[PDB]
Image 1 (tube, rainbow, N blue to C red):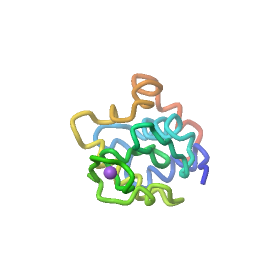
Image 2: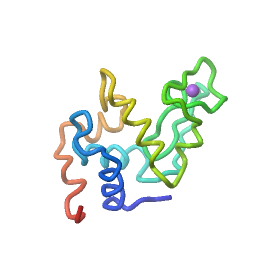
Image 3: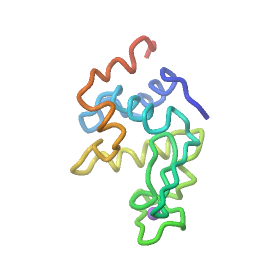
Image 4: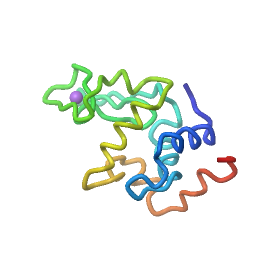
Length: 129
Ligand code: NA
């Protein structure tokens, strides 16, 4: 499923992400924009055998199990296929676990490079939240 920007903003707010661990809602929408272009089916297969899954491109080396990544952990304790759903709930719950560590949203390189330090509120501007 390909969310609209404002549709995803509303859904992330309803899933409790506004100011979660200090990151305002627009951070999360911006991260989804540059990780997956709001596509819950997005995948990115890396040549180390790991894969990034879903709207927030959550990687199978650390966070989810896909059974195809050697030496991997499953720290969100979920199958990676749960990250491909039209319901963003599993991606959001794993995202909350990832962002609660020392590096915060720096775990998302796209967020680090295209969002951090910018006026991220622009990503929720005009959305009737
Ligand atoms: Na894994």
